[PDB]
Length: 113
Image (cartoon, rainbow, N blue to C red; front, side, top):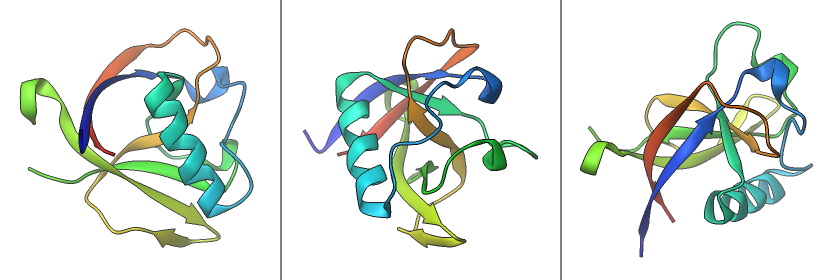
């Protein structure tokens, strides 16, 4: 399928044990896609002071359309030293590995895969 319905656990930034997916734009987009497919991806909601607590390159989920079965359509945009790789809508949050942190909520997304 071109799109996959996912429910992403929303994590508090101070709980996150693994604070990024890797060391290049291409690696983090790769790893984020694999974790999204394997159900091992968390979402951190971006506010003042969140991003400096996480590791670059960042992977964002961004709204790609203006929501089938409650799932907001999103795509992946990566960021390194203030340059973004991809073009999309508003940020729903930053993706991180999920290694068993307790979530505060779930964000239903339809991921363009």
